[PDB]
Amino acid sequence: YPECIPLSRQLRAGDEREHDRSRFWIHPLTGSTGLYLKVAENLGDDYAIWGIHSRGFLTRHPPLKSIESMANYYIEILQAGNATGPYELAGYSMGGIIAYEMARQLQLAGYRVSSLILLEPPFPHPEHLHQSSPFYYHDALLMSANFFLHYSLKDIVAAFETLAYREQELMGIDADKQVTWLAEGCLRKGVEQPLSVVKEKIENMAQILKHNREAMAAYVVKALPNAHDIDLHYMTVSQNRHVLGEALTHDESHCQRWLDYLPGAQVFRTRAKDHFHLLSERESVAMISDRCRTIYQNAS
């Protein structure tokens, strides 16, 4: 299925004539699968997994609006390529919400889900969530520019905290000239790319961050049809980036709220510093990858 662009191969599994297409990982808020590359690395020799990006992340395509909509489209990516076989879905933060909604939509039809791995998916409660409801588009521009800054400059030699932007930098800048201001400063910081290119990619991903964050806020968590049919796994932590609302930041309350929908789920805990460091701290990724291996190992 080459035409389903949002999907990418996660492994050195490019040479296989026939390969298993049942393990899929779903993007978080940014829409990228870069957080899953190391987890894939430690799993390359045994089991093959695939990553899904947001619609319009790599391409010039229009994003999707609702969690139910993106779920349905990536099921097409799953079913086209794997006609009937059971699927194993995983997701971090927003991705866990999506993979959960797929297990809903997959089980609503005649299809089966073998394993569901939720890496700290936040629990949105629409009212209390939208009762506060502070979100601004210039915040998404901040996350997009810093994501571009960190990704473009991967040279550790010659700090990134001074490289990153801050909200107070846009205080006296009009919203129309904000994307140009962030792109101009990117070139000034050593990005060395055409200004028109950085302007396009900052705003294009910022469009996805706004749509992905808005989709998380409108989601209504529903019960899984036949939830005991799934191998349920919840991966959490022990015991800036404020585009996500205060109610979208993953707490232990979100984990406890999710367990009411996931009976018999096995809670896996790592020593990560935070929810944002769950797939960033070297050892936390190793604990997750080792646990992920056992789950995929338990395929019948």
Image: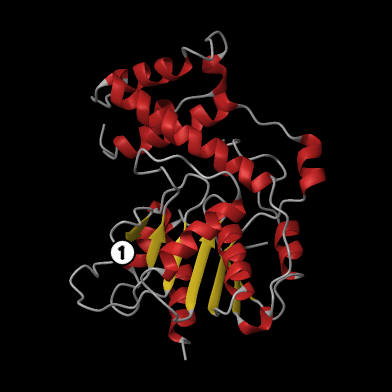
Taking the spot 77% from the left edge, 47% from the top edge, the residue there is 126
Name the residue carrying label 1. Answer: 1
Instruction: Examine the image and state in which quarter residue 297 appears.
Output: bottom left
Looking at the picture, tell me which residue is in the foreground, 74 or 14: 74
Can you say whether 154 is above or below 14 in the image? above
Q: Where is residue 28 in the image (x, y as percent from the top left)?
A: 51, 51
Q: In which quarter of the image is the N terminus?
A: bottom left
Residue 88 in the image: x percent, y percent? 48, 74
Q: Is residue 128 visible?
A: yes
Residue at 55% from the left image edge and 70% from the top image edge: 117
Residue 286 visible in the snapshot: no
Applied colour scheme: secondary structure
Mark 1 packing: few (<14 Cα in 10 Å), some, or many (20+)? few
**Residue at horizontal 45 percent and vertical 33 percent from the top:** 144
Q: Where is residue 114 in the image (x, y as percent from the top left)?
A: 53, 81
Instruction: Give the x, y percent position of residue 71.
Output: 55, 58
| The quadrant where residue 45 appears | bottom left
Q: Which amino acid does label 1 sit on?
A: Tyr
